[PDB]
Image (cartoon, rainbow over all chains, first blue to last red; front, side, top):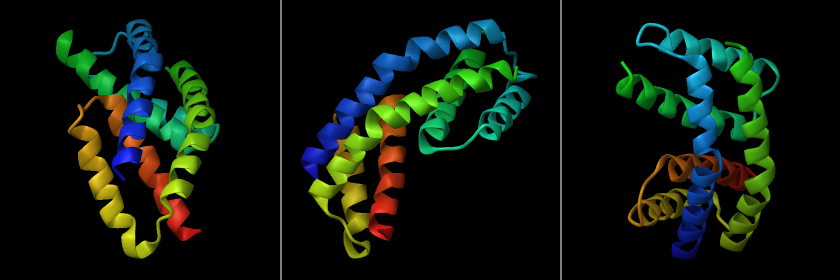
Length: 76
Length: 74
């Protein structure tokens, strides 16, 4: 339990360090606003899952959406 | 774009390859059943976040929980 919790922390911190900078760049090429962010996310979800759905892709979309939310906060 | 959906698939498929086998190993060392999955998850969750919380840890917990549910379903 406590040991697996720490291993999840290592995986979690690993996910952060690997892809967080990749999301920032994906948001720059996007240039989203407070009026296209929801439709962009919804269309991106359909486009992603059309080629297949797995837990990694769901987890990638959730992290991207959270980073999308932060980007629209900071540059809106 | 629909162009971004294709790059998320690459990240998503990479996330699956990178950690799915590690999630399997952590689960078969933990050996959970239906009678104990909920308490194990909720204690694993709090202990994880009391060391710090960021979006990677949140999604790692979500993916772990999904594979946890799959392990108990056997």
